[PDB]
Image: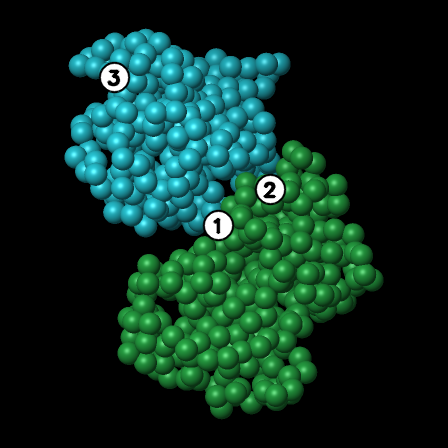
Chain colours: A green, B cyan
Amino acid sequence: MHNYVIIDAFASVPLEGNPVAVFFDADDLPPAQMQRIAREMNLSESTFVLKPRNGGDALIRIFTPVNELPFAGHPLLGTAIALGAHTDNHRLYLETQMGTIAFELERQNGSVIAASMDQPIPTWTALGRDAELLKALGISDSTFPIEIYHNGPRHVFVGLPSIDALSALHPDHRALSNFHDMAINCFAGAGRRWRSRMFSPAYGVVEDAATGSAAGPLAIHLARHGQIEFGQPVEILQGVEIGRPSLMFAKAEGRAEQLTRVEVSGNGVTFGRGTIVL
Amino acid sequence: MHNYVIIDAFASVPLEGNPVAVFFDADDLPPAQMQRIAREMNLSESTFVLKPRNGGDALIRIFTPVNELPFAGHPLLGTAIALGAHTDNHRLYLETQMGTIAFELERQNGSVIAASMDQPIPTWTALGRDAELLKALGISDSTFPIEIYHNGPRHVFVGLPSIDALSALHPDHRALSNFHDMAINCFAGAGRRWRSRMFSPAYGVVEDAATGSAAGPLAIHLARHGQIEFGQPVEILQGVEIGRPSLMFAKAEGRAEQLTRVEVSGNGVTFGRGTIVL
């Protein structure tokens, strides 16, 4: 049998944020069985906590209902928060396919309520399909350059001139399906405070509550395009329009040509706990 | 807090069949909150066990992640099996939007391992879009007439000349998306033993493991088209190609013009059990 918890990542209130199922003591499960369990659960992701193999605290394997992922933000944040119930350590080193990711855990009375991660440093370039993407979103132009970032998944960013213009988007999801192996992240805001919406046929989601692997890239995007400085944190509120508000905090240190750290943080809360029969 | 179980319906082995989450003691939950919980879980359906209002044993409300349903086969079968852990009764009367559905529970040593339901009697007519549907499925013709049945959801049936021809189907799901408010059920077999595959963009599933509300209609279809008699049971094995084999048993009594009973039965098994925080 295995115990699991469901964590709503990037939220402090259950039914907000983005759920992940975290399965403990998973070393007896072959990967094909982990994949079947992730399919059974049908959450965006299920993760599995394994013994470490390179000096970290644990090895985490991440599965959607259909495949394994090398890196994912909200699922790793939820896993780190879940593992709080089982360690006293202030820092947690989680091994993944992209290497060991360092987390700082934040507690109140023994309960981990939030965590911060250092993400893989992305790469980026211009999308080069702007008219096609804009048509699919139903708008004429972006504010800032339309650029696509890679840190495992790929995330394209399209800027809107106001929060209301962002909420008014009703994309043609069929048209968006021509954009393979990426998520489309539309954003608006000013200063410290930004709003986002994410759409991805390629990743099997009509609209995502909290895209944790897009938060680091967005901070970089905003700094490069002069809306914040490198080293300044931003608050990104996602998922409001779909009723799953999610608050992500991000900061990118260094400069565009030499990034030294990309930090993403948020709250997490337990929605449920259970046991499975295998 | 609420307790729940995950039942794999139309299976006796966990990770086979079609999952449903069953939430107990749900009378304190407003429907908008039931809908939010069903969305959180993201299973094809979550059900909620409520006090009866018209003389049954319980009232069951059925939700997909996006809406409430009046009737659904695999979710009601799973609910009846789950409720076995909480009653000694041989029969269970479950109130729904389509009225009270009678279940017979089958136990071994106190555990309910299977159940039989009397389904709403469907109606049917020719689809009248045969060339369009056949093109979408990638085939030239059906064996038997292409007819669409209604018992809450709508189910169209297209016959294939062999089980291998059925397994070879690779439908164009975009083309299938032009068929609104229905599921497409392709079938093959002979005598007592049939195979099916179900596809439905309209109902949010690429391919379904076990379509319980299609089993009763299929028995009627096979009887009307002379492949079985009215009153003769069939075994329908679904979901083999997607690795979620599901065994459904169905029988239609009477004659086409005066159906007296449509029975569907199957096994169910618990995959997991848990508690949520609201």
Amino acid type, label 2: Ile
Subunit ID for the residue under disc 1: B
For the residues carrying marks 3 and 1, which lies nearer the camera in this image?
3
Could you tell me if residue B244 is visible in this image?
A: yes
Query: Which of the 4 image quadrants contains residue A59?
Result: bottom right
| Disc sitting over residue B225 in the figure | 3
Query: Which of the 4 image quadrants contains residue B150?
Result: top left
Say if B12 sits above or below B27 in the image.
above
Say if A171 sits above or below B240 in the image.
below
> Mark 3 or mark 1: which comes first in sequence?
1
Q: Disc 2 vs disc 1: Cβ atoms closer than 8 Å?
A: no
Badge 3 element: loop
Label 2 sits on residue: A37
Label 1 sits on residue: B40
Subunit ID for the residue under disc 2: A
Q: Nearer the viewer, residue B252 or B160?
A: B160
Q: CA distance from mark 2 to mark 1?
A: 17 Å
